[PDB]
Amino acid sequence: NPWNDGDAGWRGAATGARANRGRGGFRRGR
RNA sequence: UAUAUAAUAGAAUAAGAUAAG
View 1 (cartoon, rainbow, N blue to C red):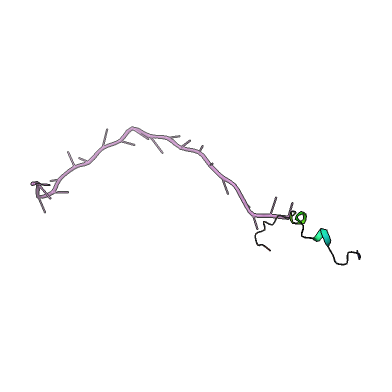
View 2 (view 1 turned 45 degrees about the vertical axis):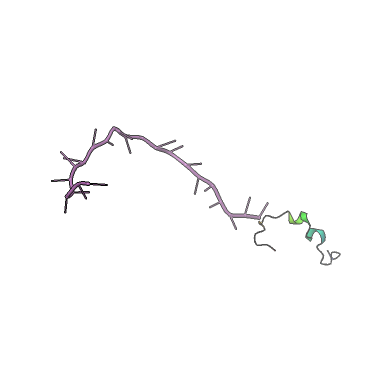
């Protein structure tokens, strides 16, 4: 899709919904 | 889409000299 123009947006944002769909343990830490 | 859990037992029965206050 060209209209996205390299912008993931909400699907690739930092929102709590996207940060609550992984199980890594947050051990190493960003 | 993750690297991890830990429980079964039993027996009846005694040796004995220190150069002291």
